[PDB]
């Protein structure tokens, strides 16, 4: 497991929803994306 | 007016100055002479503003004396070393502008603190050490145009009442730890300049953040 690794996976998770990454923390297992779609 | 020298002089003794001084606040002289450091007067007749900036005022302050200045409309105590919770500003009923930027005022401001301050137009509480929630009475200020509370230790949700503030044009709550979801009313509001950045856990309409954790 890893922290920065987690945010990259968050980034990808967000990208496969057409959204930008917004919020990421490994300790809280929270990855949040934007509401808006990529421009 | 000379009579207005009495409350100011009392106020001068109720604070600890550690840089410069207020020796130009001489009891029995009209504070509107032009000789008083930091005094603004309306039409050069009656004291309407007090500006005691960068004097290293430290410890607790009391402002009660200032209620005897009928035309006092602005106070600026920016850039000092004030700490403790807010003094009795609410006794200064005609106050239009209150500036406390860059001090160490602390605690959670009691929700009803501002109820008696219906004339406030500008409120700067930024760069202090306020914690807990935004007091609900701030949202009830019918004349408020600007609120700056950036750089404190604030938490909890942002009250939706902000969206229904007729005169509000500037709302800076950045770099706190405000929480939960942003009320839609706030995003809806017409020509409002808002800044909610550096509140990590905020989600919703203005910060542009889906609330759902996708992990």
Image (spheres, rainbow, N blue to C red):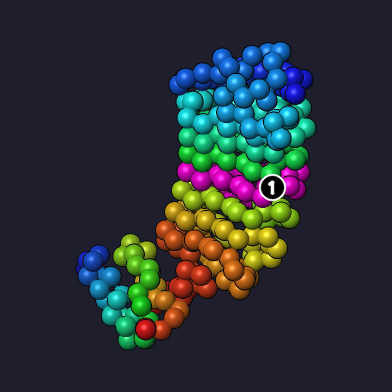
Q: Magenta residues: mostly which secondary structure?
A: loop
User: In the rendered view, does B148 fall on the left or right side of B32?
Assistant: left
**x and y percent of residue B68 in the render?**
76, 27
Could you tell me which residue is drawn at 47 percent across and 43 percent down? B127
Residue assigned mark 1: B120
Vertical comparison of B5 with B187: above or below: above
**Label 1 environment density (alpha carbons within 10 Å; few <14, some 14–19, many ≥20):** many
Helix, strand or loop for disc 1: loop
In which quadrant is the N terminus of chain B drawn? Answer: top right
Magenta segment includes A38: no
User: In the rendered view, does B206 fall on the left or right side of B31?
Assistant: left
Range shown magenta: B106-135
**x and y percent of residue B24 in the render?**
58, 17
Q: Nearer the viewer, residue B173 or A4?
A: B173
Could you tell me which residue is drawn at 47 percent across and 30 percent down? B54
Q: Nearer the viewer, residue A33 or B102?
A: B102
In which quadrant is the C terminus of chain B drawn? Answer: bottom left
Could you tell me which residue is drawn at 70 percent across and 35 percent down? B42
Residue B11 visible from this viewpoint: no
**x and y percent of residue B30 in the render?**
70, 20
Vertical comparison of B71 with B214: above or below: above
Vertical comparison of B116 with B17: above or below: below
Which picture quadrant has residue B33?
top right
Vertical comparison of B59 with B129: above or below: above
Q: Chain of mark 1?
A: B
Residue B52 visible from this viewpoint: yes
Could you tell me which residue is drawn at 61 percent across and 73 percent down? B188
Q: How many marks?
A: 1
Magenta segment includes B115: yes
**x and y percent of residue B163 in the render?**
64, 66
């Amino acid at each position: 497991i890893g922290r920065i690794g987690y945010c990259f996976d968050c980034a990808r998770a967000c990208m496969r929803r057409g959204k930008y990454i917004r919020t990421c923390s490994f300790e809280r297992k929270l990855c949040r994306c934007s509401i808006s779609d990529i421009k | 007016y000379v009579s207005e020298s009495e409350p100011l002089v009392r106020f001068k003794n109720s604070v600890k100055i550690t840089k410069g001084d207020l020796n130009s606040w001489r009891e029995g002289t009209d504070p509107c002479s032009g000789k008083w450091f930091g005094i603004y007067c309306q039409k050069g007749l009656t004291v309407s503003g007090i500006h005691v900036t960068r004097l290293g005022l430290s410890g607790t302050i009391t402002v009660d004396d200032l209620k005897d200045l009928p035309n006092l409309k602005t106070i600026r105590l920016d850039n000092n070393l004030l700490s403790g919770p807010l003094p009795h500003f609410f006794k200064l009923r005609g106050l239009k502008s209150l500036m406390l930027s860059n001090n160490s005022f602390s605690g959670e401001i009691r929700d009803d603190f501002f109820k008696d301050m219906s004339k406030l137009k500008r409120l700067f509480l930024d760069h202090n050490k306020f914690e807990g929630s935004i007091p609900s009475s701030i949202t009830q200020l019918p004349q408020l145009e600007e609120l700056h509370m950036q750089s404190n230790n604030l938490t909890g949700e942002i009250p939706p009442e902000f969206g229904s503030m007729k005169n509000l044009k500037v709302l800076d709550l950045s770099t706190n730890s405000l929480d939960g979801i942003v009320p839609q009313s706030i995003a809806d509001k017409k020509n409002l300049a808002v800044n909610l950045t550096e509140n990590e856990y905020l989600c919703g309409p203005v910060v542009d953040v889906g609330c759902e954790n996708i992990e």
